Amino acid sequence: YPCPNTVDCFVSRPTEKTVFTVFMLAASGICIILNVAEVVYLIIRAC
Amino acid sequence: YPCPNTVDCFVSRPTEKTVFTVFMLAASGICIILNVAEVVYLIIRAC
View: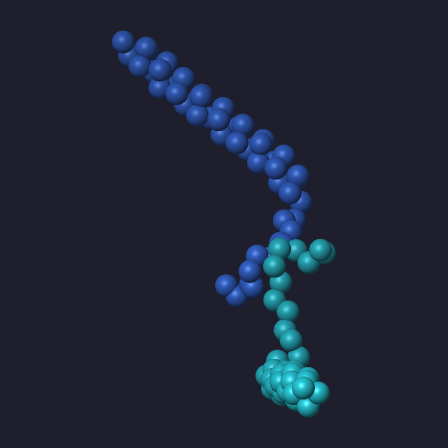
């Protein structure tokens, strides 16, 4: 509402946003892996 | 085509056109009945 039925809306710079989305998500995934390795390394260091 | 998905289009004077449609169709139906009566009356006159 209030758009009647289904309307076609166009996203600004879909490909450019997709490229930066891939870069940011890949960096976030690297952060997740590094944080997991950080926990494992610290646990190994303690034990 | 080319209207995307379904669009809402508005008819000009829908009620006024409906009223005149009823008048014309009723008159046409009267013409049909009168023509049938014309054929029957002429057949009866011949026989």
